Image 1 (tube, rainbow, N blue to C red):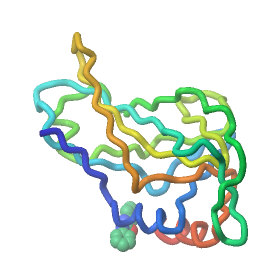
Image 2: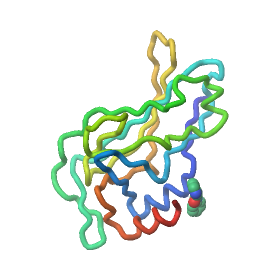
Image 3: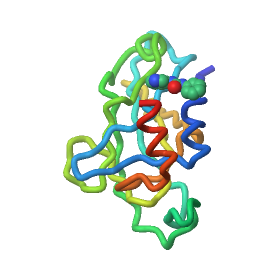
Image 4: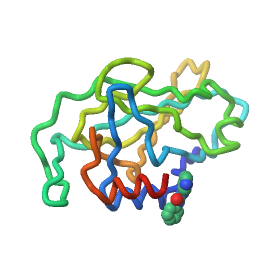
Length: 171
Ligand SMILES: O=C(Nc1ccccc1)Nc1cccnc1
């Protein structure tokens, strides 16, 4: 049976209990923590691609007021459909299953200035989503997995001083 497990779930949850934040910039910014998954129950002989996107969690934006994240207004129109292709793609099931699959190079941005970046709206909450695509499949079968532990608010600057400190500390 196909099983996709979050790596470092305890680390993610240290950030989630503060409400996690990720910086977006013009030129794009890497995530900490990095999203990493362990995979079992692929066909080791088959070839797959791994894709990453970010799903908008709410019909509203957030604001950090008096040390509390609270609903902050109506949402911006949805960021365009951005998908990140894992740079190991396409590859054997055996390749994906032998070691955690790491999205260490994905950059989050708030300007559509290209470079395979993920466009997010500042002060909106997003949940990472991984897709497994089988190569050469006439049915174009896809699997999609969400990672609730990894939810975060996109920000141009850290709001929560505990997040700023955690980010310097564990990284
Ligand atoms: O700090 C880490 N995990 C953790 C933190 C607190 C409690 C239990 C586990 N992992 C980690 C990952 C990547 C680089 N450095 C450290």
